[PDB]
Length: 129
View 1 (cartoon, rainbow, N blue to C red):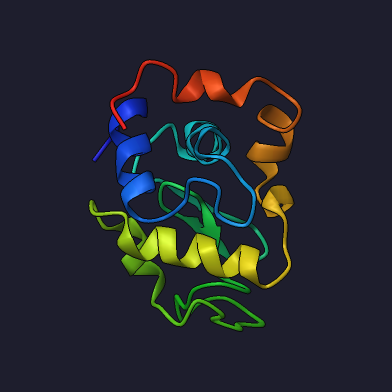
View 2 (cartoon, rainbow, N blue to C red; view 1 turned 90 degrees about the vertical axis):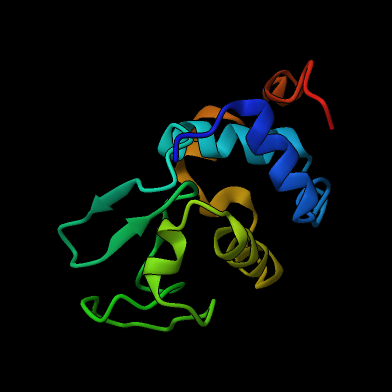
């Protein structure tokens, strides 16, 4: 599924991301825009043998198990395929885990490059929430 910004904002809010560990909804929507272009099936296959999965491009070394990655920690306790679902439950819960394990949204390269320090409210502006 390829989300719209406002549709994703509402789904993320229902799943508890708005202000989760101090990160506003706009930060999360912005991160998804630049990580995956809102596409729940996005994949990025890295040369280190890991892969980034789903709308938040969560990586298979630390976070999810794909059975193909060295050094697997599976800290979200899911197969990476769950992160490719059209429903965002597993991706949101794993994103919450990343932050709640002391990572900032710094963990997302696209968030740091493209969202940090900017008017991220623009990404939820005008949306029904």
